[PDB]
Length: 119
Image (cartoon, rainbow, N blue to C red; front, side, top):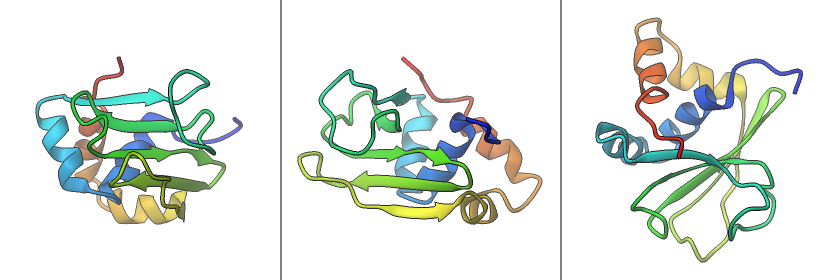
């Protein structure tokens, strides 16, 4: 912990970085779930309390794992469910300066945080 931001707020940046259009299509109809891995369901290695973005209908379709630790985000995404994740490490600053530059944008980004499902 001892961090800043909230995971909710960071995941939008992490998926605007990785298929922003797929993030948008799903938020348009609220079809996007924000949920945590946990020792809960079938998952790959190295995500043990990572947040994962998927749509409720896109299970095998497309998926984006992320976790902010400190001032880094390790985005772990794939286009094939049955194979391991890629890795994009960025600083939390990188993502903020890509998808949180302006003041007006702080609406839209936080709007994508408030048009997700959580369960």
